[PDB]
Image (cartoon, rainbow, N blue to C red; front, side):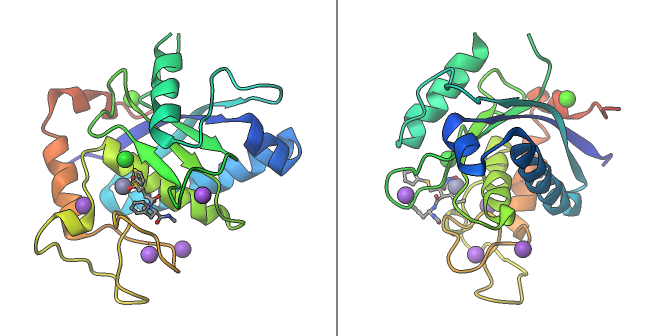
Length: 201
Ligand SMILES: CNC(=O)[C@H](Cc1ccccc1)NC(=O)[C@H](CC(C)C)[C@H](CSc1cccs1)C(=O)NO
Ligand SMILES: [Ca+2]
Ligand SMILES: [Cl-]
Ligand SMILES: [K+]
Ligand SMILES: [K+]
Ligand code: NA
Ligand code: NA
Ligand SMILES: [Zn+2]
């Protein structure tokens, strides 16, 4: 099939901003993260392109709660209330309850509820880039590797975990399991996946 493109809109909340210090430090870090996300998805004939960026240097336009569900719902609610993107990814400096660092609306890509929330949990920008690729994967119809029986992951190194494992562990994931790929292909059957057909400029 032809290359698919995610036109991505990133929002950085107040906590994240005050954590990085300045506007340039955030732009630098966002470009880092998005560059790696795009790198991970190139192995799926996917391009992830940043088309918009919003930094809340003063206050958040909605409540970012320690609970990912709340924050995610607040994002989708706030977003709906314009642009032209396919997907919205929130990056926060708020530490989510427990060990949770990401949450997403499943199979919502291209819909009005197309979004996810990501905590910048690691000094390495790769940390939040893998989380977002994972979350973005949910938006694209992917489940956890452990929820698909006989799912095969071709990661030869570390613990052999892939991007869509329900837990990161001690090493950041690098590839997509075979079930990830299969589920993404199924999602690309849905007529709603049409918004991924347009290559930006
Ligand atoms: C470093 N932290 C982790 O590895 C935790 C570990 C964990 C696993 C299960 C339950 C709670 C915590 N995993 C996540 O943060 C997942 C995202 C990662 C894999 C990118 C995240 C867990 S989902 C929920 C957790 C609690 C309520 S809902 C997920 O699946 N989003 O897509
Ligand atoms: Ca599009
Ligand atoms: Cl989720
Ligand atoms: K890596
Ligand atoms: K999967
Ligand atoms: Na936490
Ligand atoms: Na891992
Ligand atoms: Zn998940």
